[PDB]
Length: 506
Ligand SMILES: [Cu+2]
Ligand SMILES: [Cu+2]
Ligand SMILES: [Cu+2]
Image 1 (cartoon, rainbow, N blue to C red):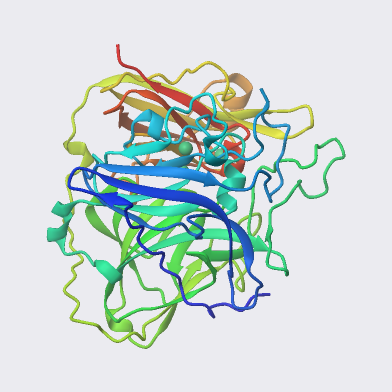
Image 2: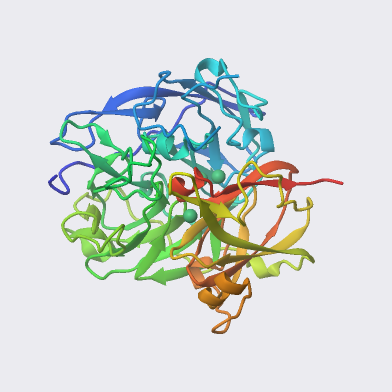
């Protein structure tokens, strides 16, 4: 049992360029086995880190800044987490990596395609690898992005090992809004972990009470960590000044969804979603945050000087939350003296509505969340009962707008992520699950519900709840090529709830 709120929240340093000109910014990031202490009372933990850090360095760019990152593997040839050899079938290395800039409006060969992996020093490369140095032209709205490993059949492990980091796009136009900035703009990467007494990470090599059918190790369909970390520390505290802060909240956990509140009942102000500023600020007492979602929020500590306020969590993982463990994320202490006047603002009017768009609907895809069961008895989670390797069926035309209607007859929520694009949420609508399973027929049991205000901006990872049809609309561009869409519960993604998405150009 690890005592809460005894370590200061780390704030990862901003990565510095290896070279930089007006025309181009060039970075190098090397994946390394490293060691860091995750809590005061734990021995140091073995981890895989971008530049030896967990989380990796925060990367800061401007809109349209012409960025290059050479992501390099300098990792050991064997993994320290349990590899399931049965889920994926010219011998390949055991350890493979590839970096996805999540939310990036990125050319396809710089997107971190799962089969564009590489081993150490690029010695072996996957069949879709094209380049060492990834290109991020950043021709997109200011927003909270994040970067993480995306390698075929290894994503859950490589991310759990520590390969996650923040990437912020600043649009200079935003600066007139005078949102809290500099030291008052802080990323919060939330990752749940289970840690052994000797400090080493625990990741299960099989489900609990394994049928002796199962290979060993075997993938599991879900992972819930006993402990919550923010920016690489267990249940940390952050000293803040009694003023407005902006927080870039990122769910970088494998499976766990959070439902966040402040334990004094105080409110957040949501200013942004995955795809950038909301049209209007939204005052919220709590919010849901599934894997890979980002909330850009203001918290105003002005009236709370001296207080300790816990960022709390009501969502369970595999059970009800426990008040003494996973009900806690971190603790704010409003005890830092003001370094200057708070000149920041919490404005109402942030940006254009998505509905200012009037694109023609080129196509409507109906998609279902399902799966089968393998030789060993395990669930294999599938998008439209296709395997990753089946020929591509999601094939939007570049420059066109589609509506995707995602049908979820399963028992749980799935956070669905589309690469390249951000999209708008149209509505959700409940249906008869038994009927749909029995007949394939979709019968609605209620009217369509528009998105809550949090989802009236631009999203790239979206919760598809059980027993609902979710509809989204996306314009596919500006690049054509081979991308992916998938569930972002990593245990599902790897087996095998991920499909190719080809954006075609005549
Ligand atoms: Cu992602
Ligand atoms: Cu899923
Ligand atoms: Cu992805």
